């Protein structure tokens, strides 16, 4: 191995470049009165230009020593490796719990120098909190601030949290905060830093977070973008509103409507009568321009739907709803809506019912998200299995870090049973054995109904009756071929279930042939009789359907004690190391009702950890500063010395011994249940159970196998050992694995399209929120530039030299820009063609802005820009994310052959966007010109 | 589940029932009537009429089937079991019938073969090798002939003659490769007396005997025929020099014709019009006669024309940038080099000969067919095998055949054990030997399967060289030792020295110290181990008679195989070695035929010989004697047969209670099906039997196809080198590795068909365009021929005779372009309607004139010779252009595969360019056929 792979020659170089050096410098470093000072010094050294790589040894050594002084755990050489891998922005694969947490600090420190920020994510809040406080002293001991985010945390706490040197958050939490930040209104809503703000991440359970959890995106559904009431009331007004004629010689627009020349696209409802008529309905003319920007929208769109969109020509309506039509192919547009929200408007005009449900407001995929960090890395006991994915999607390579102590755990094969019912009976049987022997046990299920059902079998013994009986009638059928007196005697003893204790069967053993066939059935019947008795005798459970993360964890920490039997539901006690007799936990429990934990954590635990360790010297100083008199010092020696002896009984009784009830949807998710045992060189074993009925085999096994298996007619009660069976099992788990792979591969495909789309709109939103006035005003003017340009230019730019179009270029610019200039445009415009038209207008436009920078002092004018732009963009955006959702779960129908659905989607997607931007820029301009500050 | 539900639910149950209802029961109802028929031949000839009267082949099935069964019953002596009648229907339904062992399959063929032979269009039955083709054919001959059907059989050695005769028979037995190449050959034939397949149908219906092997485990590569280089370097470079020695000429002046040898295309047109007879005459003076030039030197004209085309109408450093490599075309599309793209018509090497760039001198594709697209050609395909349901979706999708799982005759009872994993391949084998010895000593027959010959022999050595089993013995000895000396007494020291010597240890040496054996596990386990090894050795030394069968002599081994079912036998079948010979628990008719070989031969008397051998064993004193009379069978032969037979009946009885065959797979194959067959060799018809595979982290599967991560994790796991391995990670990795392979091969063939699916449409056309001309439908030959003149001329003139700039534009270049491609001329009136009346009445006024000249040529050389020229010209043009395409494509596949521009799959680019070259190629063909038909010289 060492000769062969990457994961060996590599490990050696890590020892050479990291381990040995950090060890060589432990001497010097331990003779430092202040590690904080040393760290503060390193920050300068690095800020002096010293690479983060070169400083690694020092930093690492210092963190180890700080860990040694304020926490009391010297980083094992291999943990120093995990650290480097982490810093190297890779995945460090490491087997059990605790090893992982501490390894984080190593890299966490080295990179916290930059003070740009450091994020450490875990599967749940509990652990975030835990790991944070648990490792707090090592961090503080070097001068590092501990930032922790829990779900309950408020926008405030969150911001403080990320502002700390190191932050502990769950992936979903850190996730949505990213999305929220890009949905923020006031800068005092944003939580992440602005400086970096997703600098470096260290994912605690990568494979779980970036794989078994990255099969779905992060979605925030909002209420319906404004309800049916306003949409239908906007249709009625459209018809009540009479129709108008265009501009005559010198005399202006007729009524409310100024059509687009049926080929142009602009709906110019401008006669103030029209404006006034509409507002008279539910608002004031004032409110209409300022603040009712969304209403104008709805008004504008309503008239646009009626007037510039021919119903049965541009879209054929059916009992379903409005279905757009393509002038492209001369067909219906399958599941395609209309931009700016004009869709429901065209529905409101057609009296077609509109939706009243949620919709996407912001969406990100865990993949693309973590892809944003300046540097990502992570850890887990199971990851090499998916290295090629990690490497390819997140860029991280996987490094298989050496264990501290050789694994000794005895992972047994599987045990297959035809019926799930039979599989469980088998499981109880295992359990009872281990209980009676005194070896602890930890069963893993995949559901709560299953966890409890297991419970009930163990608690009421009346459930094991069917087994007993089934083993009884089996013994029976082969048995009565034997007729004598003695036989008839046990024939009635066996006509009653309970009489059957072990003593009832002992006397007739004389009738048992050594020969296989029958003794086999007799040993079977005897076994069951015994099992029942054990059951009845009572087996203490402790089920852990992961509901109260904190409560169960404590219960988990003690699962390593001799007669314990824990039913962890689904990764229930995920994160709490199970040692063979839990010591400091119920030690703290004693110290709870005396000298609390919170405050004195620096000493309490270092005392609990010192006593158990047996350091009369370090234990006493801590005892002095504390209120610990002999009575407490003794019950600790008593609990401790009792546990050492339980360890001895257990640590020689076998070990933990995990029992998986059924296999998971991935070898890694179940290689972890086995992982819970034989932690650090400890003894231990594992064994999985399977049934053709349990999950894996029916949901993901082929419909042909789930059929062949049955017809194979396997012996319902006893174990199954057959090629076809073990073939199909091992293959089913792989189908699923692969299915999920696909399921997520496609999710990223889709969200790659969106990325470039988010990219822009997300940043265009921030330039305006960052508030760079200079950059705000510049950009704002830029939108006036393009709108006006292409607007007039639409037809003011013909190859036909002077003659062609002039009045439509006047009104189009007149609407989008309240101001006016009108006698000299004709001069240079109707006479001198296309080049000196576009640039003679830009200049005039600026002049008006400047004058407006006088009306409302310059401060308010940009204030309007901020209000206007955001309101326009984010109002248009939400309608896109909606339009897209409806496009994905629409165009997926078997469209035209070979052109992948995707190609069609990508094509249309990019289209809608560009169009959307058009609408944005254009609308920003207009509204900046026709708004009313007051 | 199992019983009622599945029967309420799916396919392979509800279907079987319907088969029973519509096929089985009816055919049984009619056995009475049919058996009272003096001649089944007559009945069949009658059915042929009934069908020819319009009776669907479906409706006649029961009758036909019943008749085939009875003929089978009379002339062969095996009534088709009800399930076999099903297999037959499924076959006829053009599906895959899945059936477990050997013989059931062969006879099931006859059923459908008969029903469809009515049409007399032909029937093909293919198998994995010649031997079986031959075998199945003669073996089932009587059933066939008994109904009036001709038995056609093709072996590799068969000559083009026999082959043709063979295919002309009602039914033909051929191997897939054989039948495959004959397809390609027929499309490379020169004279019609070289073609072997019928012309009538000629790939009518096929019944693939071992479908999964033929269409999957054998369909990963194509069928290809590479020929010599399309004409060598000499002629290509000599055609370059002539091009430059040949001076340049000026076009047509007022009324005075072309100047020297060259008439350029207007630099934008495309035609090279070398027409001054001086030019023609100068070139021919080099190596031929002016005559030979037009007639017969069609390929030379080509090279001459192309050479001048390369020099004059293709700007070197503008259309293609040359490098130290070779000429690399340039695209005016993207303004870049054209990666690995050659030039049409073979103009490529011409442009290389001009640039003095070295030309190839190697083979190239002349005709390629993938087994997939090939069998896809049959009017109706079907097939059979014990293992196929596994790949149904493939069969369904590619060949359209569904898979039907036909019930077994007698319930399977074979005991397929799990696998046994060992860390070292060496340890795995030690283990294997151990198994064999046991089975030997007990007397249960054994059939070991390997995957190579080295392994087969190696195993062999180990058995005949008991020298090789000592390590085991010794290793089991020192293991017993280490846990043992914790016990010190007198008795222990006694066996401590008996064990300080290897041989003393016979079973007798260990029997006395059994008194020191604790019933308790730990040690007795090591003692039973030591005991076992000691026993094994003695058995080995006693000798274990092998019989290795590395599939070399198909016929010789087969006989050896047929007897593997006898009590003390131990056969080492290499890789599907004895594939096809049912290993009964005592081989009867085989060495019965062996006895009758050196007396009354098989061939001729096959109708009686075998029906006699099958009757005697069956025990039919009545039917046996009549056959004996017609034969030269006196008591002596009749007895050794009763002796052989009665000896086998009782060996059948011993093996059948000693366990059964029991197959031992040495390592797992590259597919569950390929190894479910090795297990399949045992427990044939309801028979007893067992199986077990062995595995090692070192054997093939695990290193070639197991992940580089697994092949590493496994090792570090530090497994106990000598004893069995039972671990999740292990069994996980195994089952999963076999799947990687399976899937890999799947891909490997999916892409083969992808490329060759592109080619299919391409072969499709040119292959048939070639046949219309060879089928010689004069009517269709002349029509088609005229059609090429039509398009050439049309688009030619039309290229610039159809402008938007009304009369004025281009006229002289339209004259010479058509003047070269058409020796004849008309020149003062074209200007009239052409230079004056635009584009519609230009193209159609030329077609008409063209025909007139042809008609006049149909007089130079009478109408019969005119078509003869067409035949000679067209084929010569197409197939000369084709070979250059197949070349250009090869070079395109193993060229464009480089990591081209990103996401656009290499394929998409290939598909695109592929279709491009073709279209272009067609252009060149049509155009060139026209020309050559106009400028040739019959004499």
Image (cartoon, coloured by chain):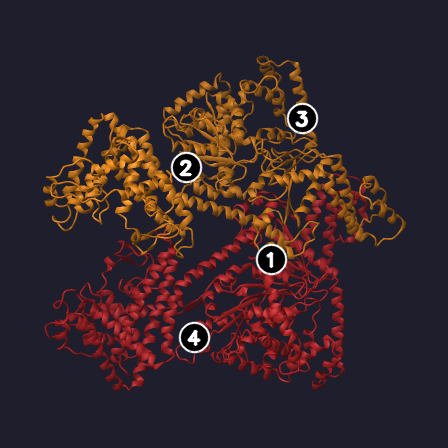
Chain colours: A red, B orange
How many numbered discs, if any? 4
Name the chain under label 2.
Answer: B
Of residues A251 and A611, the one nearer the viewer is A611
Name the chain under label 4.
Answer: A
The kind of secondary structure element at disc 4 is helix
Residue B251 pos. (x, y %): 17, 44
Q: CA distance from mark 4 to mark 3?
A: 87 Å
Q: Which mark is residue A181?
A: 4
Q: CA distance from mark 1 to mark 2?
A: 46 Å
The kind of secondary structure element at disc 2 is loop
Q: Is residue B69 left or right of residue A475?
A: left
Q: Which mark is residue B648?
A: 3
Name the chain under label 3.
Answer: B
**Residue behind mark 2:** B228
Can you tell which of label 4 and label 1 is closer to the viewer? 1
Mark 1 is surrounded, within 10 Å at the Cα level, by few (under 14), some (14 to 19) or many (20 or more) other residues, namely few
Mark 4 is surrounded, within 10 Å at the Cα level, by few (under 14), some (14 to 19) or many (20 or more) other residues, namely some
Q: CA distance from mark 1 to mark 3?
A: 57 Å
Can you tell which of label 2 and label 4 is closer to the viewer? 2
Question: Eyeballing the image, is B130 above or below A894?
Answer: above
Q: Which mark is residue A123?
A: none
- Whether labels 1 and 2 share one chain: no
Residue A506 pos. (x, y %): 80, 50
- Whether labels 1 and 3 share one chain: no
Q: CA distance from mark 2 to mark 3?
A: 57 Å
Question: Eyeballing the image, is A802 above or below A928?
Answer: above
The kind of secondary structure element at disc 1 is loop
Question: Eyeballing the image, is B647 above or below B342?
Answer: above
């Amino acid at each position: 191995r060492r000769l062969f792979d990457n994961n060996e020659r590599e490990i050696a170089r890590y020892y050479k470049q990291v381990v040995e050096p950090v060890n060589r410098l432990e001497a010097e470093v331990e003779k430092l009165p202040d590690l904080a000072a040393a760290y503060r010094e390193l920050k300068e050294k690095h800020e002096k230009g010293a690479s983060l790589d070169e400083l690694l040894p020092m930093a690492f050594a210092l963190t180890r020593e700080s860990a040694k002084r304020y926490l009391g755990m010297r980083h094992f050489d291999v943990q120093l490796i995990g650290g480097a891998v982490l810093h190297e922005g890779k995945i460090a694969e490491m087997k059990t719990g605790e090893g992982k947490t501490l390894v984080a600090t190593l890299a966490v420190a080295l990179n916290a120098l930059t003070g740009k920020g450091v994020h450490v994510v875990t599967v749940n809040d509990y652990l975030a909190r835990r790991d944070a406080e648990w490792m707090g002293p090592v961090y503080r001991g070097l001068g590092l601030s501990v930032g922790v985010i829990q779900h309950a945390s408020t926008p405030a706490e969150r911001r403080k949290a990320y502002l700390a040197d190191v932050t502990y958050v769950t992936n979903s939490e850190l996730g949505f905060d990213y999305l929220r930040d890009n949905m923020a209104i006031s800068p005092d809503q944003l939580v992440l830093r602005h400086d970096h703000p997703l600098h470096y991440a260290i994912i605690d359970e990568v494979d779980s977070i970036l794989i078994d959890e990255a099969r779905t995106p992060l979605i925030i559904s909002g209420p319906a973008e404004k309800a049916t009431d306003l949409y239908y009331k906007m249709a009625e007004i459209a018809k009540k509103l009479e129709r108008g004629l265009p501009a005559e010689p010198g005399v202006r627009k007729e009524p409310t409507g100024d059509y687009t020349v049926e080929e142009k696209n602009r709906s110019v409802h401008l006669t103030l009568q029209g404006i006034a008529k509409a507002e008279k309905l539910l608002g004031i003319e004032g409110l209409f321009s300022p603040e009712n920007m969304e209403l104008a929208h709805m008004l504008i769109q309503a008239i646009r739907a009626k007037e510039l969109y021919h119903r049965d020509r541009d879209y054929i309506v059916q009992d379903g709803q409005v279905i757009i039509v393509d002038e492209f192919t001369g067909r219906l547009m399958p599941g395609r809506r209309y931009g700016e929200g004009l869709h429901q408007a065209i529905e409101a005009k057609e009296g077609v019912r509109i939706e009243r449900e949620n919709q996407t407001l912001a969406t990100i995929t865990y993949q693309n998200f973590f892809r944003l960090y300046e540097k990502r890395a992570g850890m887990t006991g199971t990851a090499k299995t998916e290295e090629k994915e990690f490497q390819e999607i997140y860029g991280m390579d996987v490094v298989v870090v050496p264990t501290n102590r050789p694994v000794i755990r005895k992972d047994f094969p599987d045990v297959v049973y035809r019926t799930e019912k039979g599989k469980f009976y088998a499981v109880v049987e295992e359990i009872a054995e281990k209980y009676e022997r005194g070896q602890p046990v930890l069963v893993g299920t995949i559901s709560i109904e299953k966890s409890e059902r297991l419970s009930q079998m163990l608690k009421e013994p009346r459930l094991y009756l069917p087994r007993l009986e089934m083993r009884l009638e089996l013994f029976k059928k082969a048995s009565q071929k034997q007729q004598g007196p003695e036989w008839e005697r046990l024939r009635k003893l066996l006509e009653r279930p309970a009489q059957l204790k072990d003593e009832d069967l002992a006397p007739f053993e004389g009738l048992i042939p050594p020969k296989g066939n029958l003794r086999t059935a007799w040993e079977g019947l005897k076994r069951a009789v015994h099992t029942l008795a054990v059951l009845r005798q009572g087996i203490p459970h402790q089920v852990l359907n992961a509901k109260h993360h904190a409560r169960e964890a404590e219960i988990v920490a003690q699962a390593g004690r001799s007669k314990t039997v824990t039913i962890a539901t689904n990764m229930a006690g995920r994160g709490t190391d199970i040692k063979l007799g839990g010591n400091p936990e119920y030690l703290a429990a004693a110290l709870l009702e005396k000298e609390g934990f919170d405050r004195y954590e620096w000493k309490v635990e270092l005392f609990i950890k010192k006593m158990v360790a047996g350091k009369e010297e370090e234990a006493r100083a801590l005892a002095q500063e504390l209120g610990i008199r002999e009575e407490l010092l003794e019950r600790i020696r008593e609990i401790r010395e009792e546990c050492k002896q339980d360890e001895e009984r257990v640590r020689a009784l076998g070990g933990l011994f995990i029992i998986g009830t059924e296999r998971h949807e991935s070898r890694r998710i179940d290689n972890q249940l086995r992982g819970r045992a034989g932690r650090q060189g400890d003894p231990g074993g594992s064994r999985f159970y399977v049934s053709f009925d349990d999950d894996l085999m029916r949901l993901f096994a082929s419909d042909r196998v789930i059929a062949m298996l049955d017809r194979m007619g396997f012996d319902d009660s006893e174990p199954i050992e057959h090629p076809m069976v073990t073939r199909s099992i091992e293959r089913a788990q792989k189908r699923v694995e692969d299915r999920n792979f696909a399921i997520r591969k496609q999710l990223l495909q889709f969200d790659d399209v969106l990325s470039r789309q988010r990219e822009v709109i997300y940043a265009q939103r921030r330039l305006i929120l960052l508030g760079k006035d200079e950059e705000v005003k510049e950009a704002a003017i830029g939108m006036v530039e393009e709108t006006v340009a292409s607007l007039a230019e639409n037809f003011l730019n013909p190859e036909v030299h002077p003659e062609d179009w002039d009045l439509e270029g006047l009104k189009a610019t007149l609407l989008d820009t309240a101001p006016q200039l009108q006698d000299f445009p004709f001069a240079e415009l109707r006479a001198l063609k296309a080049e000196e038209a576009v640039e003679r207008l830009v200049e005039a436009a600026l002049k008006a802005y400047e004058a407006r920078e006088a009306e409302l002092s310059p401060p308010l004018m940009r204030a309007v820009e901020r209000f206007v732009i955001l309101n326009v963009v984010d109002n248009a955006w939400k309608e896109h994310l909606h339009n897209l959702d409806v496009l994905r779960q629409g165009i997926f129908l078997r469209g035209y052959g070979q052109k992948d659905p995707f190609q069609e989607y990508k094509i249309e997607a990019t289209r809608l966007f560009n169009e959307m931007v058009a609408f944005i820029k254009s609308e920003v301009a207009k509204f900046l010109f026709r708004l009313k500050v007051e």
